[PDB]
Image (spheres, coloured by chain):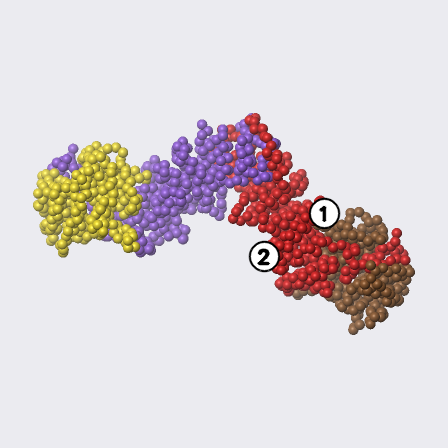
Chain colours: A brown, B red, C purple, D yellow
């Protein structure tokens, strides 16, 4: 097993393997990103990335067909985009539109091209492209009252296009805000922006994370995670129908819940909590969620 | 200002996590030191219906799996497992299916027991000569309703039944109820059995919804109820696998009811016996209940059961696969990827490709499945 | 004896007769046939050949009214069932209720039913399974044991569950339960009637009726009361707005099976009544497979009633467009034309021979029947000129 | 009405109208036949025919298409045949084959041509043609033991010819003898004569007459009449089936029965009896025979 001790002297907020599992990216209150090479059981520091002016909260890798590209977000309200060329790292883009902390950044399904979803404490969400061959332009929407803690893409899907009797793609994402709400957003070519599809109420305190399952199955799954110490699982039988709400388990968790992440096949849910434990969950025959393993080290 | 856990999945069958101590360490490990692959998915005989398939491997695989499962975990309800095994074997006698749901043999001892055959005092009623004449005269004048009313008011349920037979299944049923309930669970059971083989299963079952006392009984004893019905089916040597229409009606109606009480497993058991196809179209017109998958779709059992159930339908050459479960098959292939089983993985993506390309390239399901299939296929190389 | 004067009598083709009757010098007399055979206004008034399309359903419907009136009025004792039955079917003014009431006036019974009836309590006089036996029956059924379940219900004389269990086993044992309930125990004839009604609407009319043959006591009852029996069955037929003339198969079996029994017991008017109601075709073929009984004609083929009834019955079938006619009665039609000749009715006579010609020429030219009818038709035709 | 008093001074045995009902023929123990013209209500003697040498028992007219032809039979054992031409009568043929009284003579259905059936006390029956354009030849068969009192043709009918898969005619006649029996005869081309089809037993004394109904209906009807004072009605449902036997009425008649004759339509039966009364009979709905009129003058 690969162990990395002391990647930062300060708090580590995120660590993410790239697609081939041979680079690791880590980020800290020390305002830096670090890129580690992982080849077999060994590891080595490749480069430290400086640029942010406050703690870096999250990072996300872009799909390998776009090359070797990382995105970072920070308390300083900026999103930075980094590329690896001929072994060396550098900064290639800056997304600086928000007037308060940027809490999450996430690359969209590769079907949309290199495109970013960005969530901020200023209450807004932004979506901007990455290009080296052209001019970009952000779409900025007012999402949540007190602030947005998290935003996550739904999988690419094709839907029926009525107005023209053909097929159009439906781009959706989900957001979670300091207003205790979860919201679904859908791009609308007429409005030229993302518009509110649904408002899901269930939590009694800030929503810290939302993760839309990449399940290839027809039903849709969302996991939302709150400071109310609960995890809500949202399902939708039909693209155009209502959302079902279900508590992962009937009783409050011991501490606050922080992150939620689905496995690639979309059946396993891993929860990061305040009790400093990661818990895995999956459905039984009757559809009830049950322990699927743990990491409590 | 607090150190939190970190966990992320990788497309490379690796995982990254960090768990704050009770200097913070980050670990990267193969997904199987976290998740341990069931031998179930690994041993399953590739994609069924894929014609490189021999019904051998499957029949044996079910034996093995069922043995290991029950042996290692006695508490696991194996009804569905064993039911699907039977139907897979063509050795399907209604009596065998019945005995699987509920074993009537426990009753054979009670029946063999000594019974007092002593002459009894009168405890029922019977029309006297007068009333008997009235009934005849009523019938001679074509008055069914007046004849029945008189037989019931004198509590003579024999002629009541007779007269009732001249009037249709409807009032026939009402007479059955009055005879049983006039003056416990005994009545409920007998009533249902007699209703089913008359065509009043719809009526009989619709009664549960209104009575919380009888609905609790029905849902609690569904196994022995269905078993009673099946074991009373007239054996037809010509066609043994065909289901009496009135029995098919009962199964579906009974299933619907069970679903309405969250007994999805029980419902699926009945839906299988009746040979209800897996699809999104509400199995019954008068209700919304659908049969989308045997048990929760996200479970491994469901993946396998669903594909086995499909294989069984495949016997009939006219039959052409299911659509509602294609997503589940792709999800299956995805699950193989995560368990580092790229080999069987492509066996599925490939088969599924031809499977999907045999659909209208204009449909929503087609385009979506195609995209999703590409993504998984890409990941497997 | 050869030295003795005997009577003499001979028919002539010229509607004359010759006779001599020795006295109580012997006279021979020659007189027209009708000073000896009193002719019938019946044959004379009948609206030509029916089916001949110069026919208007008017003349016929009115002719039946007239005839039926005159007949019953002049001879009250004459049974008019068949007359009136054929009239109904001719009108489409026919309902099973109407046919039922024709066979048997039920109004006598309505009086009886209006008479006040005791709706009071009663002492237990029957039997019913207790909790124990009730459990046994359920367990028996849970094990698929119909036979043991029924045996137990019958041995405790609980005919309710007996009937129920019996229904799971087929019409056969169902019927046996009915018998045991009725006859288990003057009230003799009551049971017979009820038994039959319940048998018919279950499909056991064959069985039910076959029982008569073996019991001389119940066969005398059945043949003596056939009118009210059939009437009971018909009036209990479930009303059908779109099928007013659709006999339910089980009722059809009963009519034929019972129409056979009556034939054996000598009652060929009765039998024919049932066959008419059942719309059984007139032919040479047996009415039932397991029987030799034939529905050849309504009443004795030689009777004037039979001639007319048979042709009217044929006309009724004719409104069914597919229907081509009863070959079996063509001889009777020619015989009809012959009867017109003898009564000096050459006019109506040729109306028949002509119609019958086209009727016969539309037959297989090489069949034996065809060849004979042609000859016989020629002979009559010749005589009528 | 036409009345003829004193046609003969001796017993009158038969009187028969021709086909058009305009000639009457009468015959007597005085050995003669008389021919009366009947035109309207009037009558006149046309001719007395002499030739027989004993009482003349019966006469029969041939079908008009053969012309105006009479046949007579007599105690003297001869059958004489007479023809009317240009108003005048004469003898044209003699059938003299029997060695005892000839009791009946009857012309066959016109389908067979002018052909005679003859019955005798010598026990035999003969069948002979009448021709003026050719040579005749009698067929003579032994019919009844003690003698034959009567013989009557069955109607012309066509039957199935199996040997050749075609149609042939079946010639039948019935006889009644002093042996109490009734017998049906059928011509057989192979045997070149009439052969015994059936022997009908029922009477307990001589049979005086038998008459085969000319009924155009399918069923066959015979009336036999005996000195046992009874009348038997024989029926046959099928040309190839058995003969049913029925008493006309259940009780003996007052005296002996002498003649029986069917109306042309074949439904009415007229009985000549020893009580010197003629009774008419016909079937009711149930097929029982009942009075249809009387002549008792």
The image shows residue D95 at horizontal and vertical percentages of 12, 48
Residue at mark 2: B319
The one nearer the camera, A173 or C303, is A173
**Residue B171 occupies which quadrant of the picture?**
top right
Are labels 1 and 2 on one chain? yes
The one nearer the camera, B171 or B50, is B50
> What is the crowding at mark 2: few (fewer than 14 residues within 10 Å), some, or many (at least 20)?
few
Q: Quadrant of the C terminus of chain B?
A: bottom right
Nearest to viewer (mark 1 / mark 2): 1
Residue at mark 1: B72
Horizontal side of residue C214 vs B10, given as left or right: left
**Could you say whether the residue bearing mark 1 is in a helix, strand or loop?**
helix
The one nearer the camera, A25 or A213, is A25
Q: Chain of mark 2?
A: B
**Could you say whether the residue bearing mark 2 is in a helix, strand or loop?**
loop
The image shows residue C26 at horizontal and vertical percentages of 13, 38
Cα separation between marks 1 and 2: 37 Å
Residue A251 in view: yes
Residue beneath the point at 59% across and 30% down: B114
């Amino acid at each position: 097993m690969v162990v990395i001790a002391n990647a930062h002297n300060e708090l580590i907020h995120d660590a993410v393997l790239d697609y081939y599992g041979k680079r690791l990216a880590t980020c800290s209150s020390d305002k830096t990103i670090k890129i580690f090479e992982v080849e077999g059981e060994t590891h080595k520091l490749i480069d430290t990335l400086t640029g942010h002016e406050g703690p870096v909260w999250r990072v996300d890798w872009a799909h390998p067909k776009f090359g070797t590209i990382l995105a970072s977000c920070s308390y300083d309200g900026k999103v930075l985009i980094w590329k690896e060329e001929n072994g060396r790292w550098s900064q290639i883009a800056v997304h600086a539109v928000h007037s308060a902390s940027v809490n999450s950044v996430q690359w969209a399904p590769h079907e949309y091209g290199p495109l970013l979803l960005v969530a901020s404490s200023d209450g807004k969400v932004s979506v901007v492209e990455f290009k080296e061959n052209g001019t970009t332009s952000p779409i900025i929407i007012d999402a949540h009252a007190i602030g947005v803690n998290s935003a996550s893409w739904a999988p690419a899907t094709i839907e029926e296009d009525g107005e023209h009797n053909g097929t159009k793609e439906s781009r959706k994402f989900v957001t979670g805000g300091a207003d205790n709400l979860v919201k679904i957003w859908k791009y609308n070519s007429d409005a030229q922006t993302y518009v509110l599809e649904s408002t899901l109420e269930g939590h009694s305190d800030w929503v810290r994370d939302v993760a839309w399952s990449p399940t290839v199955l027809l039903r849709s799954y969302l996991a939302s995670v709150s400071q109310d110490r609960t995890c809500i699982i949202w399902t939708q039988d039909n693209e155009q129908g209502p959302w079902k709400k279900t508590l992962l388990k009937e009783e409050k968790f011991p501490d606050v819940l922080w992150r939620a992440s689905w496995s690639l096949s979309g059946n396993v849910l891993a929860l990061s909590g305040g009790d400093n434990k990661v818990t895995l969950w999956k459905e039984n025959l009757e559809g009830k969620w049950e322990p699927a393993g743990e990491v409590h080290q | 200002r607090r150190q939190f856990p970190i966990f992320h999945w990788s497309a490379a069958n690796k995982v990254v996590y960090a768990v704050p101590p009770i200097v913070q360490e980050i670990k990267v490990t193969p997904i199987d030191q976290i998740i341990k692959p069931n031998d179930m998915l690994k041993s399953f005989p590739g994609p069924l219906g894929s014609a490189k398939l021999k019904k051998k491997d499957l029949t044996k695989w079910m034996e093995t799996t069922i043995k290991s499962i029950s042996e290692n975990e006695s508490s696991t309800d194996m009804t569905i497992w064993q039911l699907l095994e039977m139907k897979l074997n063509d050795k399907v006698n209604w009596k065998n299916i019945s005995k699987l749901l509920y074993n009537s043999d426990e009753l054979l001892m009670y029946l063999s027991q000594p019974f007092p055959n002593g002459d009894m005092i009168p405890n029922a009623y019977r029309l006297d000569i007068n009333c008997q004449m009235r009934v005849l005269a009523f019938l001679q004048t074509g008055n069914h309703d007046e004849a029945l009313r008189l037989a019931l008011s004198k509590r003579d349920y024999a002629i009541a039944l007779l007269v009732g037979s001249l009037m249709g299944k409807d009032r026939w049923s009402e007479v059955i109820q009055k005879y049983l309930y006039e003056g416990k669970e005994l009545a409920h059971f007998l009533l249902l059995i007699f209703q089913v083989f008359v065509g009043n299963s719809k009526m009989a079952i619709k009664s549960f919804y209104t009575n919380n006392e009888t609905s609790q009984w029905a849902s609690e004893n569904w196994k022995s109820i269905v078993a009673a019905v099946l074991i009373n089916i007239p054996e037809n040597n010509e066609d043994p696998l065909l289901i009496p229409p009135v029995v098919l009606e009962f199964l579906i109606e009974f299933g619907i009811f069970l679903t309405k009480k969250g007994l999805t497993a029980a419902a699926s058991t009945l839906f299988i016996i009746g040979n209800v196809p897996l699809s999104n179209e509400p199995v019954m017109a008068d209700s919304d209940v659908i049969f989308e998958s045997i048990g929760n779709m996200n479970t491994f059992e469901s993946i396998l059961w669903d594909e086995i159930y499909e294989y069984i339908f495949s016997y009939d050459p006219k039959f052409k696969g299911f659509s509602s479960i294609l997503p589940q098959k792709i999800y299956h292939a995805s699950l193989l990827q995560e368990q580092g089983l790229n080999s069987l993985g492509t066996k599925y993506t490939d088969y599924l490709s031809s499977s999907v390309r045999k659909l209208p390239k204009k449909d929503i399901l087609t385009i979506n499945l195609t995209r999703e299939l590409s993504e998984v296929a890409s990941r497997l190389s």
